[PDB]
Each structure stands twice: as structure tokens, then as C-alpha cells.
Image (cartoon, rainbow, N blue to C red):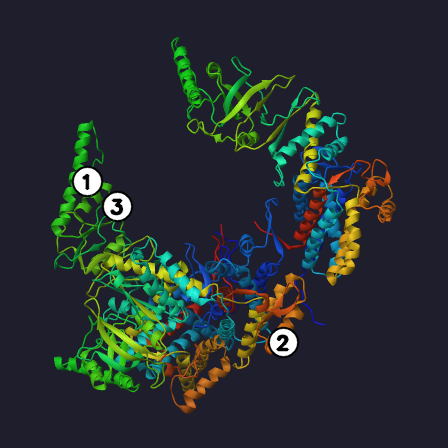
Amino acid sequence: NATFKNKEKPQEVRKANIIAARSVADAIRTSLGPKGMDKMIKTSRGEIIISNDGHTILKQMAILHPVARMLVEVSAAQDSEAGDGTTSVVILTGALLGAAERLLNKGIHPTIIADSFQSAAKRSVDILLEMCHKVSLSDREQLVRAASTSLSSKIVSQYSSFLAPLAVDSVLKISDENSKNVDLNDIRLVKKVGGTIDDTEMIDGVVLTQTAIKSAGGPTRKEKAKIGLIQFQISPPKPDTENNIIVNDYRQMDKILKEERAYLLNICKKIKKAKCNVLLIQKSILRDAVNDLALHFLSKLNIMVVKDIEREEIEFLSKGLGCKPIADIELFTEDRLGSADLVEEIDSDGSKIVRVTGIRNNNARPTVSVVIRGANNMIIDETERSLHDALCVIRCLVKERGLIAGGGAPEIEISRRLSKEARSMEGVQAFIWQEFASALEVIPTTLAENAGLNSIKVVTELRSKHENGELNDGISVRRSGTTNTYEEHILQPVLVSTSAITLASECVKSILRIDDIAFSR
Amino acid sequence: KDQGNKKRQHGLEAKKSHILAARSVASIIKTSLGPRGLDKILISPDGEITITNDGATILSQMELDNEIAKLLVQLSKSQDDEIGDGTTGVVVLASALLDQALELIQKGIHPIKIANGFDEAAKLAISKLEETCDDISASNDELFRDFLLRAAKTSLGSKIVSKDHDRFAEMAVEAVINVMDKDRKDVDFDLIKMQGRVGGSISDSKLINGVILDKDFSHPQMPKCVLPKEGSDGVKLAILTCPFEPPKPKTKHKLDISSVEEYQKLQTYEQDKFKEMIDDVKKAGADVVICQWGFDDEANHLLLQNDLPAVRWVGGQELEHIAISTNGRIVPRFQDLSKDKLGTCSRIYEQEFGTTKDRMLIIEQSKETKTVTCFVRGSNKMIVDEAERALHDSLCVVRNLVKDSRVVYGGGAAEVTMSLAVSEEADKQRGIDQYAFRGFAQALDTIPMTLAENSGLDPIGTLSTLKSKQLKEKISNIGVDCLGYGSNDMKELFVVDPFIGKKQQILLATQLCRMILKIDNVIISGKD
Amino acid sequence: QIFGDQVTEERAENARLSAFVGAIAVGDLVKSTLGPKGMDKLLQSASSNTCMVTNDGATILKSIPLDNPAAKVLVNISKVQDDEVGDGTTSVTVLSAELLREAEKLIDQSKIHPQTIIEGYRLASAAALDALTKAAVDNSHDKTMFREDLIHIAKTTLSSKILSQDKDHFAELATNAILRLKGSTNLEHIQIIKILGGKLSDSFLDEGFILAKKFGNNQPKRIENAKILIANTTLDTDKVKIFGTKFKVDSTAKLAQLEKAEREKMKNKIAKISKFGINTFINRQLIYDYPEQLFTDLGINSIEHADFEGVERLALVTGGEVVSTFDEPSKCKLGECDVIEEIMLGEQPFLKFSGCKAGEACTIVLRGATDQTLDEAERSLHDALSVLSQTTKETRTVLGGGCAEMVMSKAVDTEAQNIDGKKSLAVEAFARALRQLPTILADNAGFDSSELVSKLRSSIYNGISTSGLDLNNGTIADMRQLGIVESYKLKRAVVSSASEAAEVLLRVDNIIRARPR
């Protein structure tokens, strides 16, 4: 017959990128699950790190291969959207790349391969939603149990009973109804040494990251005060040229002292004009925040000062408090100031955390700032990351309601539905539906391998019982065998399996779109 | 000194190397010869970017270590001032003489015999070409206007000018006649100024009878037009070779200011000199002041109140063309001005060109001047430089048409007639020079064969066909077809080449071919 | 070592490969990215962490450093296409590479002159643009509402302009200056007459081609059944500057005898004028009374000082030619008009022509109260005519999806039918590149191009000229039923840019490397 010539050879570029990217997925494949193998990376500086996290390994691997670098962005969106499964999405991506190698050997153009994965990803979501267990945000029983079981893998165990409703009550306020995805960056976890895990405060208004003035004259507490962000600095006169303090006379000590106190008073007077009793100054190492002479001036005015505000909180305080960053003293106005009920420094052991209540702003909405306390530094660290996973799983229920029992159940349920659907297709696509379902079996196969169980034996027992049960059949690491994952309190949200298939389908799609690699400087 | 890396050539060696060195550069320009040739991308070291097939531009940009090809650049530099459009014609003709000279060397003929052989053969071909030459002015006067327009159209047909060529064809004729006398027939390229700027199109290009100077009339409030002022004599302009400022002595140059007293006095003295220098312009009646140096801020204040526009930073060479065109004089001092020494022109005005922010001035004249500035407009800088050199090529063709009223029919018919006449007279001339005359006729056949290859025709078949049409039928001029037409006989197309132009090509080709044969040794020192 | 300082000349064997294979390799970068289903490319720098992936053809070509001196020519061609419209840069480079790919076969196994190959495309592209015109459709449908939508847009263009005094009268003049043309909308078909001593609202539209100057002294002011001849020559005092000449004569009367002999040479040209059977003659220069008096006995009216634009616009309305010379009697392109009437407007005599042959045009006479009202109106009128002409040329589309590319192939194959000897393969090679455009579009779709393009050619060859390629279902269907159309201006821009790019590259027997800046 007569077909297209194919003078160029783009396949050698794509096949070299698929094999090189498959070796990256096979390396991360051993890290799947809590029993998975840990990978070691030695940085050029000499630092050695150890962990099973897929997003951490791919970030510190310093991959030179361009296509394999996309797995870092896919794992980034995996943690940003779903929050969990960064290792599973890399395995699913490599599983589609491994299945695409047999597709290219049959003479199939990657456009049909890419268009079939997108069509299979959209239908795989509907298969999960029909088989999913429908839950709603109005039921607080399933929201607490889902967050409690997710913390069983973390240092906090017995104290996780009180930690679950704190994360639930924080999401129920920010979720509303149709808001769908709600940014988790609005939830600020402030960790500080001292205290214990059992001591927690919601503080819906906001929480700062620092203490108050420790010098002489600090009020440390104020009631019915206004808050604003100030990028300016309270300092004695400091011209752009070189300045120095040289006093050769007895009278010059009082002249320079009164001259500096006069310039500090003019700054403190303009603040009193707007009746701002709480000052937030951006942290800068160039000069100081407030001079000790100005601390006595603001003490008489009953104006609380909180300095050393990090640059990361400048954007956060401008949102939750509804204020605006103010560069200079001339830009400082009352319209940019928020009204706080009570601003006080809470006394704690080695902490001294300042909190704010009653932001009294209609434009501002219910932002969340939660304080984390603990004796050991390793506590307040992992506790902040453990609450992140608790907020992601609950947020996945907000965007798309319903939860799917983990342990390989959603991967097998999709493969069973696509096996009968592949017979209803026609043409080249019909062979891809069988290869797409074959790549989905790589995830439950790896779960059985990393757990020490027999690979094929566990997978066959799940598909054998799949004719009776439906979503209740999966892999259980605690039971070391095939049992009901719903009764073992192993639960997973639907958005994780939805995003893992969607991102992997778009990844592999964009992988086949690059047929050439050229040097461009 | 510099013993190492020293190249030395001998007789039995360099004679073969000098021919191969010429054939390398010759084969490069054979592809660009003719209207069907190749336009080459060239970038000068000054930053000018242009694309043209002109051999004078291509060969000038060629930098090479071959000493024989350097003589091609030396001849083209002298020919560029005489004609400039015959660079591709002479080098190929000179290389054809060298190719025939190498054959005579293999036959035992000394190179000095070949030099005298081509010299007597060139002088014989001039008399034969003159007998078959035709005249214009003595034939038809109205065709003389048509010959000048269609001769420029031939050079403007390979460029974007071909659409608007009708206007540029008349601009090329008037620009040459203005700078020359009919009896003297002397045209200098320095008398015709070629300038152009970005913006507008080529259809908006104007022919100016005077200088340009690229001036905005200094302060914008000054008037953009200069009136004759109620029937005065021309338009008077001032030319100053001294800058505008209070005069200072050469012995001291120092100025001491003791206090505000001497400061306020010296400030008024400098303003009093400004009032004394402007009165000399008013007493002479000069409308605009042209100086070589810039003016102060107070200078434009007094010149604006009296409605006296200013001109700043004029080169020394530009000051000469102003006094010649406007019939003025060069006044060294300020107080030596007078109505007789001021340049008198027809009018002075500032004509805005498109969206260009330059806003130059135009000084014209009704009577014939010795200075003409051709200004070209275009939408792109590359289009301006392309139409500028294309118009300059038309100025060179018309220059040779008015230099000699007798012209020959081109298109390859000129080289065939010169070859058939020498070849017939070669058998009548006996001796050793017989082969030198036969080789000269065979060397003239390289030009029509080169044009035939670039036109898509058989170089041997077409050349042999043209020789039969000019012999068995009747003696006439029928050349190879450079541009698409229905049939042969370019004489029917009225395609003419200047007799003084074609004669200048064969003389420089013979003069250089002899000089190449007069160098048997090449000494090149190394780098210390 | 010729040239130097990074400048060099490529060998005649390598230059043809650098201008063809070297240009294809540049076109191969945008080859697989053509179309909405096209692939993507990677651009990597030395740091390797700054890289990016994009399908944009203008981004890939400009970012990649090109050491090939012939590749820099395609960069300039891409800049010309980007000036026209910001879309279609990829299609031009790919089509230019297909023309150069067949050009390698047009040299090696062909032996066809390269300039004749370009002339073979000029005749093939002319038939390609004509095929796009016959198959051209438009969204202009419901023109009754579209003709009304133009007068409202013209009023919006008059905002901030001094013409805002009366919107109804001026918008009607601009609207009737476009739709009444029924042809090219370029300003060369619209003459502007700026006059003084009146009001702006007193302006009117006249299609009679009004020009300022008059003709003749004692000649009549009306001409019936006029025969117009266009030529440019100087019949009065040639060699405009006679200063410097030396006339050798025995007496002053002999000096005038040579002028009489010059007047005898005038009859040689005047006799050729009378052989054309014309009552009217056009000249850019002036004419002396003696040759003009001979025109009176022959009944020939001479319009003088028409400049050039005025001559070209006269040749378009009367269907004439701008040739300034007489090659042979009774062989030429002549114009004519029914009635030539001399009128007077603004205290100046004007000429109003009537009944031009196949004349389609208009002349907008603007009557202002000063020069500021005349200059600002003509600049603002052309801006209003440009917006109205933009809606005529754009939104007018053609059948896409491989249709128009194959329809042009049928017209080029028709041009390849009747052709001379050496251009037979040159014209046929142009139709091959036209069929490669839907072939490459079917490559990135993942289907069989050799099956679809071959059936598409045989389908349109006999009947069914509206068929095209369907990339969704992978079959051939009617483009009018599926509603797949592509802009006609985009088609003309790609074909014109491909002919301009091939004009420079095919003439190349050697490549001069550009100097680095």
C-alpha cells in the first residue's frame, strides 16, 4: 500500500525520553507505601538526606533530564491540590510511559495515544464517583474519623482525638458551600517551643509569629486598638550619607539627645493622629525597628509595638486583617487601619505568643491562624506538617465530596469497568483501553511488593473477591493480607485518585508532545 | 628581517598560480552578472545593511590574501569613480584574457608578447566597433529623451523601483544635466549628493536643486518658511566661518570676576556682543544664518525676535556647496558681510517628510546650479539604501550617454560584433601576433556565453546562432536575451549601451591584464 | 582567505544545500508544530534550568541561535509575515521549506533555470490566488444589515476629528466610497480634491475622476467619444538645461534652423500619434505651441501636467496603460470615456470625465475654509476608509481543512497543462507543496495522510470542489456542512510570503554570511 513516508525520525527522541523518565519512576516506585524502600541522595555540598517522600527526593535529585523534571511539577501539583500521593502519581506516570512503549512499537502515532489517555481519564473519574461513598460536610462524624486515622502515622496519636475537630471546625468555616477549592495558605500554623500538644487555641481572628517589646516600657497588652502594617522604620536621624556621633562638649549630649527625641516624637505624633495603638513593622536587618527613646514615647501614648514581622506574614496580615502595606509615614492613614478588640501577649513557657481577636472587618473573611505548642523541637515541626495532611484530606472533600477506601481498591475498580468497556470500542483506541487498564494495575502491584507480600498472589485474591464485594476489597498493611479496608479505618478522598489520574494523563500527554531537543541560548 | 613565513614565487610557478587566482574571483561574480543574477547580502563594518548585486560594492567588501585578485580591487576603485557599473564586466573580460593568455604561454609565447598582443587587438576592436556604432542626437531628438528614460529603466528593473521607475527615470536625467555643461560633458559624483532617510515611500522622493544640511531651524518657534520679502534679490543667507560668541583674545583666554559688579557687567557685555553680531546680519539683509558651530540659548532668543532662523553645526565641506549653488562667498569675519557676499537662492522652507522627526530644510534654486542633492524616501532603511544605489546606478548610465552621443546596442551583441571583426582580421595579420588576435576574439566570446548561462540558454548554441544572424543575413546587432521577451534582436527593443562606457571597459580590462602579466613574482612578508 | 571577520562565502555545492536542506532543517523545527494538534519543542540553555516548552513558531525560530547564514534569511521573512498579521508564521516557513524541498529535484534531476523556476511560481501563484477568489465565501451575508453597519462604524471613526461637525453627510461619503467600488479598496481608486472658499458640509461624491488642470487654449470644453492615449515625452525644449552648449553656425538664422529640424523630428512622433486614431492625448510634460497646433488640425486634445499618480489613476478608471513609449502602431492598451466636460468649482476650472470604459472608482472632493480643514480631513478620511475596507477584506474567509490547499492544486495543475517546455516541472512542483500542507496537518493528527490526500485530490478533480479533510473523524466530508472556514487574507499572506521568500533563495548560487553585530 501507500502510507506516509516518515522521513524524520522523531521516535528516537521520544523513546529516549520515555526510557529515561521510566527509570526515574522505577526509582521512586520502591518508595511507595510506609514499608517502601528509602532512597539516598548525596548533595554536591556533602549533605546526605534519607526519606521516602516522592516530592522531596525528586526536588533534591537535581535531574538534568528535561522530561523527568516535569515529575517535580506534577508532584508539586499533587501536593498542592490533593496533598497526598506524590509517589503514586509518579508511578502511574511511569506506568503509562511503559505502556506507551508497546504502543509505539505497533506503529501508533502519539496523538491517538495522548487523546486516548485524556478520554480514559475523564471516564475513570465518573467510574469512581458512581462507586464512591457519598459524604457531606454537614456530617462531623466522618470528618473527625478521617483526620484521626490520618494522624496515626504521625508522632501525635492519643492527642489526635482533640486535634481532629480543630482541623474540621477550621475547614467548615472557610469551606462555605459552593466555594469549592479554598486556599490552605489562609491557614497559618505558628509553631513555638514550650507548652504541650494538648494546649491549642483556634483564635479565628489572626495570630502573629513573634513576641512584643522586651525593653523597658513595653505595654505588651492593649484593649480596643487599631492594627496596621508599616514598612517604615522608627530610628534617629540617618541621612543617606555617612553619619557619626561625635560629642566633644558637655552641652552637645543634650543637644543631640533632644534632636533625636524630637524626630522620634514627630513619627509617634503622626501615628497618634490616626489613633493606631498596635504597630506592625516589617523585619529588616539594616537598621533597628523602634529606638529605645521612642519606646518611652509610645508607652505614654499606650501604643503596643510588635516588631520583627517576617516578610512572609506581610502578605498574610494584609489579607486576614484587611489592611494594606504602608511604605512611608506619609502613606499612613486611618482608612488602611483595622479595628481589633483585644491585642495581648499570652504568657507561656518559652513562647510568649501574641494573639488578636475581633478583626471587625466585613471585607475580611474567616481566615484561620492556629498556634502549635510543644516541648521538643521535633514535636512542633512534624505537628505542623501532620496538620497539613489533615487539612488536605478534608479540603478534598470540600471540592469533590465522597471518599474511596484505599489499598488498591480504586485502581482495581476502574480496571474491571474498562475491561468490559474496551470491547465496546473500535479501532486503534480499543487496544489502548486494555493497555490503560494494565498500567493501572502497577499501583496495587507495588503496594504488595513493598509490603513483602507476594505480588501476583495478592492481586489475584483481590480480583477474585471483586466479584462479590465492590469497594471493600483492597490491600491492608496492618493485616498483612487481603481483607476489608473500610473496617480497618483506611480511608482516602476521591480528589487524590482523581488528581493522580488527571495529572498523569496530562503529563504523559505533554511528554509525547516533545519530538525534538534543541539547544537554545 | 622577517625571514620566516616569507612567500616567494618564480616564473615556472607563479604564471600558473596567477591564472588560478583570477579564475576563483571571476567565477564568484559570474552568478551575479546580468539582471537575472543573484543579489548578495552585504554588511559594511560601519553597520550599513544592504542587499545588491553591484560588483563595485561586492568586490570592495572582499578581503583576501591573493595578490592577483587585489589588482581587481585596485582597478574597480578607479573604475567606480569613472563608471561604477562596469565592475562585473571588466573582471570577467580581464579573466577571459588571462584564460587565453595561459594558453599562449603553453604554446611558447612570452607574457610580454601577450601584453602587446592584446594592446594591438584592443585598438583594432575600437575602430571596428566605431564603424558599426550609431548616434542619437544626430538621429532623433525625441528618442534621446526616450533613450535616457529606458536606459535607467534597465538598471531599475531588477529593484523594487520597477513599479515607480517612471518618476526616478526623470529624476536621474535632470540630476546629471544640472551638474554638467553640454559642451564640456564633465560630471562629478561629488556634485550630486545622494541622501535618504527612513519613512514615507519611494513615490514621495523629491529632486532638490540645492543643499540639505538636515536642520530643524533650531528653535521651533522660528518660522518654517522664508519669503522673498517683497521682491528682493533671491533669498540671502549668511555663511560664517567663526562661531557665535563674544570674541576672546589669543594671548590671555582668562576672565577674572572679582565680585557681582564685574559679574553683572561681563554678563551684559556678552549680551551686547550678541546684539552687535546680529546687526551685521540685519545690515547685510541675510534671512537665515548658517554657522559651523552651535549657538547658545540667548542666541536663539534674539534670532527669534527678529524672525531670523538659525543653522547649527555645518561641516566645512557643506559650506563650499552652499556658496557655489547660491552664488555666495565665504566671509571669514563677522563685519565683512554684505549683500554681494550672501548666497542667493530661490526660497527656503522646512518640509515635513512623513512621520519622520528630522524635519529637514530644502533650499532650491531656479537657475542651474553646480550642486544637486537627491533625496530618497522609503518605508524601511534597507529599501532606502536599495533605491538610493539603484538611482545612483541610473546616474552613472546617463552620465556616459550624455558624455558620448554615439551608443552601441548591448545585450551581448556588442561583444559578438567586436569578436567577429577581430577574428576576420586575425588571419590577415601574420606572425606570432596572429594567435594573440585569435585569442582576443575568443576571449570576447566569454561575455555573451556568461550572460547566456545566467539566462537559461545554451552558451555555445546561442553564441553560434548570433554569429550566423550577423553574417549570412546582414550585419546588425542581435544579442542574447537578458530579460524576458518574445524573440531576438535587442535592436528592436532599443536597448543601448554607451560607446564611451563600453570603450572604457575594454581599455581597463586590457590595461590590467597587461599589468598582471608584468608581475611574475610575489613577495609577501610574514607577521613579526 | 576571502572576506574575513566571521564573514565567508559558502561553496556553490554547499550553498545550494544550505539554502535548501539548511532551510528545511529550520523549517523542520516548525514542521511538526503546525496546526492545533501539532507537537511541541524544547529550548534549553547552558544553565539548563532556564528551559521552557512551547509550540509557538515565532518563539522557537527567534530563540534558537542560527549559525546557518541562509537561516537568517528565513528570520527576515518571518518578520515580514509578522508585520502583516501575527498569525501564520509557522505555515509560511513550512510552505517555504516544501517549495525548497522540491527545488532540489528542480535542479539535480531536472536542469531548469532557477529564475524560470521563480517565474514558474509567479504564474502558478497567480492561478493559486485566482482559485482562492473563485472559492472565496464571506460572513458578509445579510449585506442589507452590513451596509447599514458600515455607516455607523464610519461615524465612530470621525470622533475627535474636525469632520465630527456633520456625521451623517461625511459617513455617507466614506461608505459610498467603498461599497460602490466593487473591487480593490486601495486608496489608488479614490481621488482627493482639496479646494478652498466653502463649507465642509458642501462636499459631494463624484465618480467622474475630477482633476485640477485643464487642457488646450482655444480647444473646446467638451469632448464626445474620447479616445485616451497615455504617454510620457518632452515635446517642448528637451534637455531642460541648455546652458554650456556651443552651437557652431555662420549666422543666427542657422541656429534656429536646427530648432526647425527638431520641429521636423516632432512630426515623426506626431505621425505615430495620429496612427492610433485618438482625439485625446495625455502627457506629463509640456508641449510647445507648434506641435500643439498640429494637434488642433488632427483634432487631438492634450491634457498636460498630470504628474504620475494622476496618470496611473487615469489608467485604472479608463483601462489604460502607463507605457511612455511607442513600440509599434496599433499595438497597445487604450482607454476611453464617453464625455469630457470642463466645470468650475472654487473659482478654478476643473475637468469632469463621464462614461469611462468599465470604470469603477470615485473622487471625493473636500471643500474646506482653510488649509487646516483640508489636510486634517484627508488624513482622517483615509483612516475611516481603512476601517471600512478592513471589514471587506477580513471576515471574508475560504473553505479550510485541506480544501483550499487542494483547490489551488487543481488550478496549478491546470496551469501545468498549458505551459512552455522548461517550466512544466517548475509549475507542477508548486502544486506538490500545496498538497503537502494538508499532508503535514494530517501527520500531527495521527492519521494516514497518503490515503486522505490522495482521495481528496481525486474527489475535487472530478466534481465536488467543496470537499475537505476532517481531522476529527479521519475522513473526507463537505466543508460547507461542517462549517470549517479559514481567512482569505491569511491565505493570500502565506502565498505571497512564500513567493517572496523563494524569490531570494532560488536565485542563490552562493551564500554571503552576514557580519555579526
> Disc number at residue C317?
none
Q: Which residue is mark 3?
A: B294
- Using the image, determine if residue B51 lies above or below residue A221: below
Compute the Cα span from label 3 to label 2.
Answer: 77 Å
Crowd rating for badge 1 (residues with CA inside 10 Å; few <14, some 14–19, many 20+)? few
Q: Chain of mark 3?
A: B
Q: Which residue is mark 1?
A: B246
Question: On the same chain: label 1 and label 2?
Answer: no
Element type at mark 2: helix
Crowd rating for badge 2 (residues with CA inside 10 Å; few <14, some 14–19, many 20+)? few
Residues marked 1 and 3 touching at CB (< 8 Å)? no
Compute the Cα span from label 1 to label 2.
Answer: 90 Å
Looking at the picture, which amino acid does disc 2 mark?
A: Ser
Look at discs 3 and 2 and give the one toward the viewer: 2
Q: Which residue is mark 2?
A: C458
Horizontally, is B289 left or right of A261 in the view? left
Compute the Cα span from label 1 to label 3.
Answer: 14 Å
